[PDB]
Amino acid sequence: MKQPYAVVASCAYCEKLVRLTVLADHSAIRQLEEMLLRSLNIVCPLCTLQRQ
Amino acid sequence: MKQPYAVVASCAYCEKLVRLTVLADHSAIRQLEEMLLRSLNIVCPLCTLQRQ
Ligand SMILES: [Zn+2]
Ligand SMILES: [Zn+2]
């Protein structure tokens, strides 16, 4: 069962919160949240272009 | 070494392309791309709110 899930994480560069939605099984969401702890950061729309 | 990486994937709901940037080590990016094959989909801004 894939389910919709709201990901919330601080931008790599500016620590603004970045919100994105994914559709994923339980284990993928658990995996993603584990990645977000240390190994992966998401980037906000402005920093994704460069200027904060 | 974390590096910036442009993720491109089709929206779960509408198959519009969704682009996001992450900062991640090699193995995390490999892991993410593996997830995107089957177990995880990202969702575009409009579908993230509901109306396509
Ligand atoms: Zn930012
Ligand atoms: Zn969409």
Image: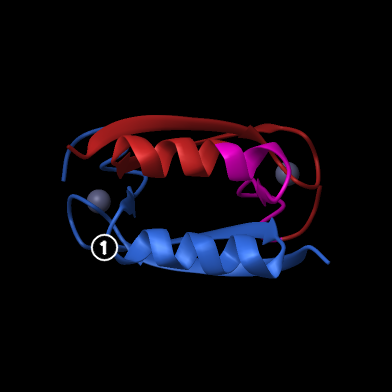
Chain colours: A red, B blue
Mark 1 is on which residue type? Answer: Lys
User: Which residue is pictured at 30% across the width and 53% down the height?
Assistant: B39
Query: What is the total number of numbered labels drawn onto the structure image?
Result: 1
Specify the quadrant of the image occupied by residue A6. top left
| Ligand 2 under 8 Å from disc 1 Cβ | yes
Mark 1, Cα crowd under 10 Å, few <14 / some 14-19 / many 20+, is some
Question: Could you say where residue A4 lies in the image, as x and y percent from the top left?
Answer: 28, 33
Residue tagged 1:
B16
User: Going by the image, does A28 lie left or right of B4?
Assistant: left
Indicate the secondary structure of the residue bearing disc 1.
loop
Magenta residues, start to end: A34-49
User: For the N terminus of chain A, which image quadrant?
Assistant: top left
Question: Could you say where residue B50 lies in the image, as x and y percent from the top left?
Answer: 21, 34
Of B23 and A2, nearer the camera is A2
User: Which residue is pictured at 52% across the width and 62% down the height?
Assistant: B31
Specify the quadrant of the image occupied by residue A34. top right
Does the rendering let one see residue A1? yes
Of A50 and A24, nearer the camera is A24
Q: Is residue B42 above or below residue B38?
A: above
